[PDB]
Amino acid sequence: RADKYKQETDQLVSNLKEENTLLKQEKETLNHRIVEQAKEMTETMERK
Amino acid sequence: RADKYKQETDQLVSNLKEENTLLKQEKETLNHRIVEQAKEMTETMERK
């Protein structure tokens, strides 16, 4: 019982941690895209 | 030891699930913010 519980819990925890890290990276990339789009689009504003 | 491992890993699994769901929701809302901001600055294009 202990061995099976340890194995399945470890697998679930590792997968969930990987998913959380991926979600954090995606959010950071979205924020960077926000900044880049705002800057470039304001530059186009000024150019036009 | 099996019981203590079970408790710790159940807490970890619950926290990881909640964090994953919250981060996915935050990423989706961030993308919605991206779309809304892009629309707002396009509208500023036509208005200005």
Image (cartoon, coloured by chain):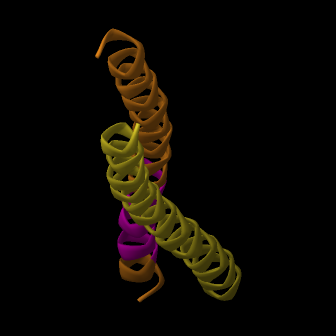
Chain colours: A yellow, B orange
| Residue B36 vertical placement versus A12 (above, below) | above
Say above or below: A38 vs B3. Answer: above
Give whichever of A47, A37 is nearer the camera. Answer: A47
What x and y, as percent, mark residue A47? 38, 45
Q: Give, as a single range, the part of the protein colored magenta.
A: B6-18
Residue A38 located within the stretch drawn in magenta: no
- Image coords of residue A11 (percent x, y): 66, 78
Tell me: A10 left or right of B45.
right
Judge whether residue B7 is colored magenta. yes
Give the vertical position of A10 relative to B32 (above or below): below
Occupied quadrant, residue B45? top left
Image quarter (top left, top right, bottom left or bottom right) of the C terminus of chain B: top left
Closer to us: B36 or A18: B36
Residue plotted at (36% across, 27% down): B41
**Residue at 49% over, 38% down:** B31
Comparing B43 with A5, the one in front is B43
Q: Name the magenta segment's main secondary structure.
A: helix
Q: Nearer the viewer, residue B19 or B36?
A: B36
Tell me where residue B1 appears, x and y as whole percent: 41, 89
Q: Residue furthest front?
A: A48
